Structures are given as C-alpha cells and as structure tokens.
Image (spheres, coloured by chain):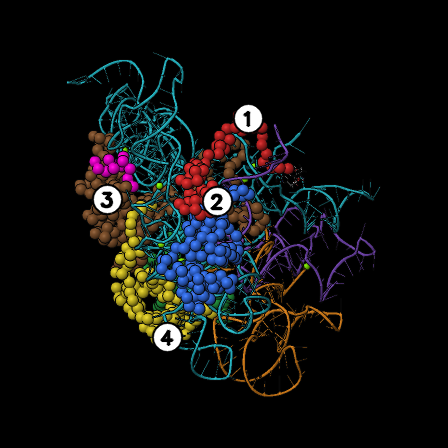
Chain colours: A red, B blue, C green, D brown, E yellow, F orange, G purple, H cyan
RNA sequence: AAGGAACUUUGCAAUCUCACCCCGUAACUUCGGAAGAAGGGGUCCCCACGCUUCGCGUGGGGCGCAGUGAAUAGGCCCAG
RNA sequence: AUUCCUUGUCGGGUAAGUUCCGACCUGCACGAAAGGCGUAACGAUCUGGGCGCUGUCUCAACGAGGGACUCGGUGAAAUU
RNA sequence: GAUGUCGGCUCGUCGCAUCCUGGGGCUGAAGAAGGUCCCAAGGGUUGGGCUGUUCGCCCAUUAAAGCGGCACGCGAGCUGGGUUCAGAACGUCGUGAGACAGUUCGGUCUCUAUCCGCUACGGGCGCAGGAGAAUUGAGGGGAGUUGCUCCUAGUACGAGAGGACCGGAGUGAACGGACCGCUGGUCUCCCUGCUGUCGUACCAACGGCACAUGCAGGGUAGCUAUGUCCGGAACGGAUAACCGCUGAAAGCAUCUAAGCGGGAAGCCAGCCCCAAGAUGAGUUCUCCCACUGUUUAUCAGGUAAGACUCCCGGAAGACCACCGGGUUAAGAGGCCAGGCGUGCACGCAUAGCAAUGUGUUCAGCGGACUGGUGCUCAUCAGUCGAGGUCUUGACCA
C-alpha cells in the first residue's frame, strides 16, 4: 500500500503545539512623508507614488 | 559549498534570452517594471551594454548587435543614449521597489536608466 | 599509479614484452636482498616501487617466458612524479624492469629513460644499464 | 602558550635552499593587550588581546568603556591566551622564531549540509547493478528488535565544516616584522581573510 | 572574517618577488633547458632537457612551462617552475607557428 | 588524472564502433553462404585539366586539434 | 538441459578456474521417430573465453538541468 | 485478521575463549627463531581466481590476514544470484492426472515517516534589573594501528653458521583532519575554432537551432584527490599478570598476615573538539541608571544603555541562524587600472586567379581575482528595551 503511515491520531493538543510558530508577523508600516497614507520601508508609497520625488503615476 | 558568483533560474539559452530580452526593453523604453530578482540580474548586463556602446566605432556597435537584435534599439543606444552618458563613470541604472503582486505574491520593482 | 591488473611495457631484454600487475609491495632493498613489506595494504605502485607480476606477452627465445610470476621495479609512469625543487616528470607509457630477489636486473640492458627516483631508491644496477636518467 | 592573532592572506610557492615550500602567509598584526586575567581577580591566569581596528562610531558604549580602561583603541576581535603574561602590547617579533614549530588554529570553511559520503567517507552504493540507493545514502541505520534504537553518535548527514580546527606542529619558514607577516609551511584551516590563532606547540616533540 | 583594510594582492606580491624569475621571451617552439642535477649525491651534474614548449601555466612565483621531448623512443614531459633553483637557463633553439596556447595535440 | 572489469550472480549498465566510397577478408559449408567477416585507407576548401550527370576522376595548392567537422549512425572475435 | 557420491580423474586455458572445453567410463538413473548421433546457415536463446573501450570498479569529483528547500495561490492520502 | 526467508552490499557496535601488536611465567629458553600458559579488548585485522554460496580450496602479500553475538544484526536501506508461485526441458517415479533427493533456462521486491530513536538547525522561556563582550570546565565526545632500515653492534651469546635484548635515529603503509600553493580533474557560455540550416535587405560581420552546452579545443575563481601540509605521542598517577623489600603466624623459610616498591598498546590524566538548560543555570570586564501613572482603569506607558525591523551583500547558509556594510558610507554593483584566460578582433591595406596568407595587432574579447573611485542602491522611518522580591549575617558613615 501507502508505506510509512501515521500510527495514532495526533491529539488536538499535539496538533496545536506544532502550530505555535505559524503566526504571521504584521508588516512594519511607516507613514509617507508626503501623501500621508501608510507605506513599506524601502518601497515607493502606494498612494502618491513618491520616493523623495514622485516616481510612479498616482 | 557554492561560493561561485552569477545566478540562472532556467537553462543556459534561456538565461541569455531573458538577459537580452529585458536589456532591449529597458534600452527602448527607458523604464520597465519587472520582478526584483529579475531586475537585479539585469542591472549589470545593461550597464555593461552602455560601456560597449560608449566606444562609438563600428566594432563597438557590432559588439552591441550581438546582444541587441533590434536594428532601432542598437541605433538608439549607439547614437542617442551612450553619447548622453559621456561623463557618467558608469551607473545609469537605478532600481526602485514597487511592492507585492496578487497572483504569485512577488515583490515588483522598477528599473530605469 | 600502477595497481593489480595494470599492464606494463618491459624496459629490458629479459625476454618479457608485457607484464601485468599482481601485487604492489612496500619495495625493500637493504643489507641482505630486497626487504620484507612495510604493510599488506598499499594501493599504488609509483616509480621505484617493486611489484609482483604475471607475464602476458613474452618473446620467443628468452630467460623469462609467459605466465611466469615475477618481480619488477617501476621505471616509468604516465602518472606525474614530483621532485623537491618543484619540477615534474611524466612519461607517455608506464614501464618496469624485471628483477631477481636481490633487486638486480634479469636482462643485460635497459631500454628508454628511467626515473632519477630509482637512484634515490638504491637501484644502482638498473640506473647503470639505463640510457638516460631524467 | 605564547600566542598571537592574525589573518590568513594566501598561499604561495617559495624556495629555501634547493627545495620548494608551500607557504600560508599570515599577517599576525599588532595585538593590543587589553585585559590581564589573574588568579587574584578572575581565578585563572590569562591575557585578553585584540585584533583588527574598529572605527570609534561603530563601537558601542559598553565596549568603549572596556577599551578606555586599558586605554587602547577599539578592536573587533578579542581573545584570551592562558598562561601567557607579556609586557607592553603583543607583536610576532621575538614572540616567534624562524624555525619554531607552531599550532595554527581557525574556523574551517563551511560546506553546509553534507551527506554521509562527503561528511564521513561512506561508500554509498552501486551505480549500476540495480539501484534506487545509487551512490550516496547510508546503509543500515541499525540492527533489529534489540536496541530498537539507533546508537547515539551515529555518523549521519549534517552541517559539515565551519568548526574550530587546530593544526599541530607547523614550521615557521620566514618572518617579516614591520610588515607584520609570518610565513608558515603548509595549510592553516579557514578561508583567506579569516581569523587565525598562531601559538606555541600544544605539546612539542 | 577579520575585516582588516588590506591589499592581500600586493601583500602576496611582496613575498614573491624574492622568488620570481624572468626568463626569455618564449611562447611555444623548441628550447634547451639546462637543469642542474645536484641530486647525484655530493656531486653536482648538469643535464639538458631540450624540446617543444607545450604549455605556460601560472604567474609570479607559481609561473611554469611544460616541455615535451621524445627520449630513447619514449615520450617525456617536464614541468618547470621559472624560479626553480635547479634551472640554470632556458634558451630559444627555434621559434614556432601555433594557433593556440596549449598544443596538447602533439601528444599523438 | 592514473588504472581498465580489478565491479559483479553476470561487463547488468554505460562507452567504444557508427554513413558512403576504395583496398582487403578465415575456419567451415547444404557450395547459396558464412561476410559488413576480420582488418586497413579515404572523406573539407580553392584552382587547373578530363568526362557519363544531380555529380565524378587526376594533378597542384590552402586551412583547422579535428573535414559522414553538427544530427541520424554495426563494437568485433573464438568455442560450446 | 541426464552424475547421487562430486569441486570424479587427467589435460587445456588463468598468477590462481566448484563453472567451461576436451579426453577417460565407475551410465545412482543415456540410447534410436516419448527418435539416436551429427550438421552449414539462422537466434532480443543459454554457457564459457578473448580483443577493444569504458566511472562497473579502485574512488570518486566537478558541472548542468528537474524535484527536494523558501514565499504567495489552491490543497489530497493510506492510517488512527 | 502475516514477526519477509539464504547469500551479497551498506552501515556499524559489542563478548573474549586474543589472529597481530603490548606486559609476563615456564621451556626439551645459549643467541636468533620458537613452544606453552597467564594478564590484556586501545587500535588493527589485504587484494584477487572458482562457487548464489556462507564455508572451503588456490594465487599474491601481510604485524596479523581471530572466533563469536546483535530476529543465523541490518530488504518502510539496496540487490535478488540461491530457495518456495504460474511457462518449459532432462533424468527418475507414477497406467494416468501429476510428482522429487533432483538438475536446467525464464520469471512485478509496494513515490509522501505520525510517535520514539538518530544527525543537523532554530523559535520560546528560565538563569531575581536592562544591556555589549571575554570566559572557567562539572561533564561529554574524537583520537588510539603498525612495518621496514640504520645506530648501538658484527657487541652480548655461540665451537662455529649465525646473531640480539635494552636504548636512540630515520623513512613508509593504511587511516584521519585541514587546505588548494603545486600536480591534475571540473569549471552549461569566460575565449577561440567547425558543420548544416534559418534570420538580421544583400556582401561582409553576427545571432538562433542542432542537449536539458550543436560539436570540438583550452580555461580563471570556486569546489576537488588521485595533490600537499599535519597527526596517533612524550611525561605523569594508579593498576593487571608478574617481579621484589621489610616480615611474623610456624625460634627456619616465606613478595603478605599488617605495611612498602616496581610493572602493560588497557585505567584516570595529558592531545584535539563540544560544553553553565552544570534549573546545582558559575566567573570577569564595561555600560545605562532610579522615570511617569486620582483611594474610578491594582501595573501598564514615555525612555536610557542596547537591540530588532527593513535594505545592499557574504569564502555564512535549505529556511532560520551567523558575519559585514548601510551616506559620519568604499558593502555590493558599475566604472577605472591591474591580474589571469583565450591567442591576434572588426575595419582597411597588401600578396594571390582563388582558397587563403601577411601587416596594422603580445591584437580583440572577457564570469567569479586584486586594488581604487562616491556613478547606482543601501532613502525614509518604525518597533522594542531597565527604574531592580524577601530573610539572615558581616562591614560602614
Ligand atoms: C507494487 C504495489 C503492489 O505491491 C506489490 O506488488 C508488492 C511487490 C507485493 O510484493 C510481493 O508480492 N512480493 C512477492 C515476494 C517478493 C515481493 C515482496 C514481498 C515482501 C516485501 N517486498 C516484496 C506486495 C508487498 C504483496 O505483499 C506481500 O505478500 C506476500 C505474500 C507476503 C508479504 N509479507 C510477509 C510482508 C507481503 O508484503 C502484496 C500481496 O501485493 C502483491 C500486498 C497486497 C496488500 C496487495 O495486493 C497490494 C494492494 C499490492 N497490489 C497493488 O496494486 O499494489 C500493491 C501494494
Ligand atoms: Mg561509489
Ligand atoms: Mg528492517
Ligand atoms: Mg592547468
Ligand atoms: Mg559439447
Ligand atoms: Mg505553498
Ligand atoms: Mg522460511
Ligand atoms: Mg609475548
Ligand atoms: Mg586549477
Ligand atoms: Mg568544453
Ligand atoms: Mg608505579
Ligand atoms: Mg548592522
Ligand atoms: Mg571590486
């Protein structure tokens, strides 16, 4: 058949313990020096399209 | 280990096709939006292309034609762009990071000259 | 780099034309005849090393005839030999000289150049018949 | 005991009399003596030495204090040497002699995850007479019902390299003080530009 | 690892000029190379190896050239460090016309 | 690299060989065969001369490590 | 492709041959259309040897691509 | 309602009734070579030919080519030769269908590991303030083999032939570790050459495709062994068999009854590596320093020293982790110079009927190497992180 197979159901406890590292880390959001919508460090502000001057359209 | 120093993600032929492909795009358009990595690999190949063109002689032209298979882009690079870069000690390529895509979730970037 | 099964050109007139390695030994030569082994492992014979061998091709009329289990000293090798100054020697073909149990040649003369390493390894009589000692 | 810190520069080919010698060049730069460990203060005898210079801006407040106490200049590398108590601020001149046998130590080049064939000189298996285990793969990890376990220590694939390695009794071929250089016969562990720890033979012959 | 502001290139070059030897303007073609065989006990011999330069690998201390000869019916190749103390002098016997740097084809 | 079956139940596997032209070819035989036996040589470019073409032969000359220059492409033998 | 005793015995080939070839006859338990002996040619047949070549091997290395690893999308299974 | 069965390979570990090497006692031990018994398990214990073979026989060596255990160790590790499926044959038995003590050729070995176990690597929290760094070593692991030659010395011994112990030098083998300077290997586009065909209008020069490099020749960094460099130890302490000192019981004798010394490749220590989750959580240096909060929100919140996040990279790496840089900037790229590799570029001129050759040109081109240089991006920010419990004692204003 399907050669190595689990021997016993993994308990609600054991299953959950394994998920103690699955939690997403929230982005470190910065506020744009211009358009004043929040942005990602080292990226162009989505809203105004600025990164010192304006690079992207809108 | 692997202390080499280059970067592919396809087969020999393809790595060269992509390089030349995007190099023609940037040189023709002046600014292209692509994947970050893809853009990173492009930066030196295109930067090296400008230096060849910065020769001005037929050989320098013919050398560019080995990578740029567009009759017009080769003229744009030879006669227009390379001369404008005359006193720039190499460096005209800048990469800005735009931000994550929907499908693959890939972080996009801009590359302009 | 000679090892059991390696076939080699014979650099003498002992009658043998081609010998085949049977055993790489830890090549004696001192006081009495040749000395007894410096271990039983030892995978490669180099120039100046003694090997045990079976004769595969022998000339009609000669001391050594086919299928004789014999001793020979390696005189030439395709595998490069390195000298203390930094110099390297390497020969197109590997060759050996059949010897008796006191390490003296079995033939009257030696053919082609021999490695200087034989001189160091105390093989006086071989190095004496030798046309060149590169 | 009498030791120093340097940087692996490279390997070259050099002659002494009529024979060629493979040499590892070490820049055993000047070492500020920064802390003297005494049985009275620390409970054992040692010297804390320093190695490459650090820009004052790059140095944090706590490390500035540690250096200012000895009144040096900030370094980057700090190591101790047991039972070695010199006077002043440690340099190879008079420390090592031309000919002296030494104990070169460093961190081996790291080869990341390496399987049993490279990591332990295994054997793997047949490349042709029927296989699914073609070359690398270990064999049997154990036995049967008996130690229904696998021996602790069992040689297995893991991260290979990037370990502390000491190479005993290396000849001091040449010394170029002022240039702060030392030529060593043979191969010291680690890569060029790596930290090296040259000392007195651990136990000389 | 020790991030010292250093020119390892030059530092190596420094401990190498004292063990570097300029030899004649040769590329392939024939040459008499005059080795000094001190190794014949206390007696210092002189043997000359004369053949075609097949290769020229290396630079600095490590620069060497490969000579190929046919001696008493058997092919011989010698590799010499330019700065080998057992080398006395190499001399262009005659210059050759080749279309590459390695000429290993001469092995057949 | 050097070695070349030492692998192994077993050269299993994987190489070598590889097209066309010329020379050449064994025991044995039901005289058909065995035979593509085995083995060896040639092969590209230019010019001039000859002919039966799409092409070929002879001469001289040229270039490369290499000329079925890449793809398709028999390993062979002895004995049961 | 038959033999137990058996790796019979002697010779061949191998440095060394429980297999293989050849003799011998003591055929446990060959034998004449359940055909006996032989036979050129044919065989993806089976056995044994040789030349060639080789990563099968001493003894493995480097390199490539596709997985394996990482992220974003969708998300099974035997088992318990 | 299934514990896969011989041999091989791979991988080991363990017993000692020890094959070698180490120490001894007796010998029908002169010496050398042995015999035999005792102590001793640290390491070592070769490659082939025949057979499915384990075994055994042979070849050639060796210090030696040990015997056993681990489900006749190991198939969720590999093989599948042997044996025990279905085809087929021979011998034999059976009237037969079939059969074996047999013999012969053939014959599917099941991608995903849940727990324990094992190798690597992180996240968490603890270690009575928050931090940067240097560390002791309780403990643990690795390693541990041996020949040959010379000197002692042609001495001891021996009638001679021969020929040492003890001590002291060298040099291998196999194993291991590191390393890439050498010698080589590779180096999937760094350089050149070559074919067919298609394209860039044509010529000339190039590009694609012929592998997931079309093929060939070479090759830097890197990685690599077949290439180098080092290694097993010396000294010590306690022992083993064993050899002895002092010495009674037993006016002698006795190595023992009390005491003491010596004595092994073994034991502990020494060598190399890990190591304070050593919850028994150790030590040293250095830094910051006592902030705010209505009996309505009983500890949260600004912050320090310091770090993380993000970015650009790395002889670090699966991911994490680790090291470096982040404009107060040479981190990476580019660019400049150099090295190194390839081996003489395109274009033009000349020579020739042409193929081609010569010059210009040690050309030209150029991955990873060594520097330099502010041309490009390391922008801008955000997040987090102390204000130190109690009891006793001692010193103190
Ligand atoms: C390839 C997949 C295929 O498996 C196989 O064919 C292998 C090769 C076969 O092996 C084999 O049949 N064999 C025959 C002998 C060699 C090989 C084998 C045996 C054991 C282990 N490995 C290989 C099995 C292991 C065999 O079991 C074995 O049966 C033996 C009767 C007893 C064994 N026990 C003791 C553990 C058992 O494992 C059975 C009978 O199958 C066919 C198992 C049963 C459950 C079955 O029918 C599966 C559904 C089977 N059918 C399918 O489509 O998929 C499967 C999984
Ligand atoms: Mg293998
Ligand atoms: Mg099992
Ligand atoms: Mg080379
Ligand atoms: Mg017959
Ligand atoms: Mg996913
Ligand atoms: Mg059974
Ligand atoms: Mg004894
Ligand atoms: Mg190299
Ligand atoms: Mg190539
Ligand atoms: Mg004692
Ligand atoms: Mg930082
Ligand atoms: Mg640079």
Nearest to the eye among marks 3 and 4: give it.
3
Which residue is identified by label 1? Answer: A12
Q: Nearer the viewer, residue G14 or G55?
A: G55
Residue E90 against residue D33 in the figure, above or below = below
Magenta stretch: give its range: D58-69
Nearest to the eye among marks 4 and 2: give it.
2
Measure how far apart labels 1 and 3 are at the Cα level: 59 Å
Q: Nearer the viewer, residue H94 or D178?
A: D178
Residue B13: image x %, image y %?
52, 57
* Labels 2 and 1 within one chain: yes
Please say if the residues under marks 4 and 2 sit with CB atoms less than 8 Å apart.
Answer: no
Which residue is identified by label 3? Answer: D31
Measure how far apart labels 3 and 4 are at the Cα level: 55 Å
- Name the element at disc 3: loop
* Labels 2 and 3 within one chain: no
Tell me the subunit letter for badge 2. Answer: A
Is label 2's Cβ within 8 Å of ligand 6? no
Nearest to the eye among marks 2 and 3: give it.
2
Instruction: Locate residue D205: give its quadrant.
Output: top left
Which residue is identified by label 2? Answer: A58
Q: Is residue B60 visible in this depiction of the protein? A: yes
Point 45% across, 66% down: residue: B61
Residue E105: image x %, image y %?
46, 69
Is label 3's Cβ within 8 Å of ligand 12? no
| Dot 3 alpha-carbon crowd within 10 angstroms: few under 14, some 14 to 19, many 20 or more | many
Measure how far apart labels 2 and 1 are at the Cα level: 49 Å
SS assignment for the magenta stretch, majority: helix
């Amino acid at each position: 058949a399907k050669h190595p197979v689990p021997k016993k159901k993994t308990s609600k406890s054991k299953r959950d313990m394994r998920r103690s590292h699955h939690a997403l880390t929230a982005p470190n959001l910065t506020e744009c020096p211009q358009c004043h919508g929040k942005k990602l460090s080292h990226h162009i502000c989505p809203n105004c399209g600025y990164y010192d001057g304006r690079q992207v359209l809108a | 280990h692997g202390k080499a120093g280059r970067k592919l993600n396809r087969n020999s032929s393809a790595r060269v096709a992509l390089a030349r492909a995007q190099a023609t795009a940037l040189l023709r358009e002046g600014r292209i939006q692509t994947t970050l990595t893809k853009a990173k690999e492009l930066r030196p190949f295109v930067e090296q292309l400008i230096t060849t063109a910065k020769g001005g002689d037929l050989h320098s032209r013919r050398l560019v034609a080995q990578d740029i298979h567009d009759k017009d882009v080769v003229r744009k690079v030879m006669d227009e762009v390379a001369p404008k870069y005359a006193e720039r000690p190499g460096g005209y390529t800048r990469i800005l990071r735009v931000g994550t895509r929907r499908g693959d979730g890939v972080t996009m970037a801009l590359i302009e000259l | 780099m000679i090892m059991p099964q390696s076939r080699l050109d014979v650099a003498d007139n002992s009658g043998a034309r081609e010998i085949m390695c049977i055993r790489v030994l830890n090549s004696g030569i001192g006081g009495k005849g040749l000395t007894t082994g410096g271990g039983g492992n030892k995978r490669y014979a180099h120039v100046g090393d003694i090997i045990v061998a079976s004769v595969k091709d022998a000339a009609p009329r000669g001391a050594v005839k086919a299928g004789d289990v014999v001793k020979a000293v390696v005189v030439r090798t395709s595998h490069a030999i390195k000298r203390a100054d930094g110099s390297t020697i390497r020969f197109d073909r590997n060759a050996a000289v059949i010897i008796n149990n006191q390490g003296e040649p079995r033939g009257t003369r030696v053919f082609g150049p021999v490695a200087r390493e034989l001189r160091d390894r105390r093989f006086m009589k071989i190095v004496s018949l030798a046309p060149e000692v590169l | 005991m009498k030791g120093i810190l340097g940087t692996k520069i490279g390997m070259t080919q050099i002659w002494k009399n009529d024979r060629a010698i493979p040499v590892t060049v070490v820049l055993a730069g000047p070492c500020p003596i920064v802390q003297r460990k005494t049985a009275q203060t620390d409970g054992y005898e040692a010297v804390q030495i320093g190695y490459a210079p650090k820009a004052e801006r790059k140095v944090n407040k706590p490390m500035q204090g540690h250096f200012a106490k000895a009144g040096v200049a900030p370094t980057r590398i700090l190591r101790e040497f047991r039972g070695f108590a010199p006077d002043g601020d440690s340099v190879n001149v008079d420390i090592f002699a031309e000919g002296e046998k030494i104990d070169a130590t460093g961190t081996s080049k790291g080869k990341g995850t390496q399987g049993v064939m490279k990591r332990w000189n295994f054997a793997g298996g047949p490349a042709s007479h029927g296989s699914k285990k073609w070359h690398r793969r270990p064999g049997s990890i154990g036995q049967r019902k008996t130690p229904g376990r696998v021996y602790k220590g069992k040689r297995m694939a893991g991260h290979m390299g990037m370990e502390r390695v000491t190479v005993q009794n290396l000849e001091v071929v040449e010394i170029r003080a002022g240039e702060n250089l030392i030529l060593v016969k043979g191969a010291i562990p680690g890569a060029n530009g790596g930290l090296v720890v040259l000392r007195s033979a651990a136990k000389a012959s | 690892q020790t991030h010292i502001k250093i020119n390892r290139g030059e530092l190596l070059r420094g401990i190498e000029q004292d063990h570097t030897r300029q030899l004649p303007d040769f590329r392939p073609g024939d040459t008499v190379r005059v080795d000094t065989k001190v190794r014949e006990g206390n007696r210092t011999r002189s043997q000359a190896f004369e053949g075609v330069v097949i290769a020229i690998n290396g630079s600095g201390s490590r620069k060497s050239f490969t000579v190929r000869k046919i001696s008493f019916g058997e092919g011989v190749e010698r590799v010499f460090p330019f700065a080998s103390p057992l080398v006395n002098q190499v001399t262009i016997v005659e210059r050759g016309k080749v279309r590459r740097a390695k000429l290993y084809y001469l092995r057949e």
